[PDB]
Length: 129
Ligand code: NA
Image (cartoon, rainbow, N blue to C red; front, side, top):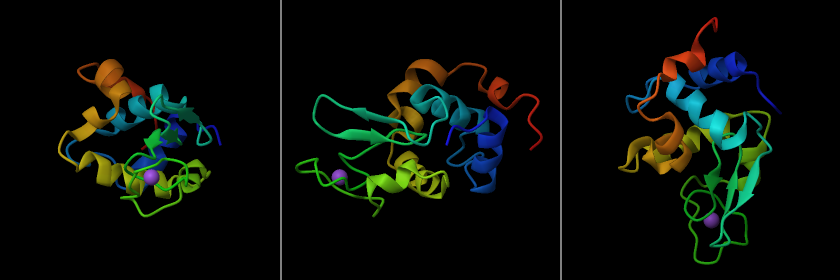
């Protein structure tokens, strides 16, 4: 599923991501924009052989099981395929664990490079929330 900007902001808010670990909703929408272009089916293979999955490009090295990332963990206790669902519940629940891990949203290199310190409120401007 390719979400609309305000459609994804509403889904993230409903699942309690708005101001989670102090990150305003526009931070999460900005991260999803540059990670996946709001596409739940987005995948990216990393040089290390891990894979990033879903709207927030969650990586198989730590967070999900894909059966093909040697030495990896599955700290969200999910198959990585769950991160490609039209239902963002698995992505949101796993993102909460990631952002709680110590480095906040710096875990998402695209958030650090393209969202951090920008006017992230523009990502929810005009959304009925
Ligand atoms: Na894994």
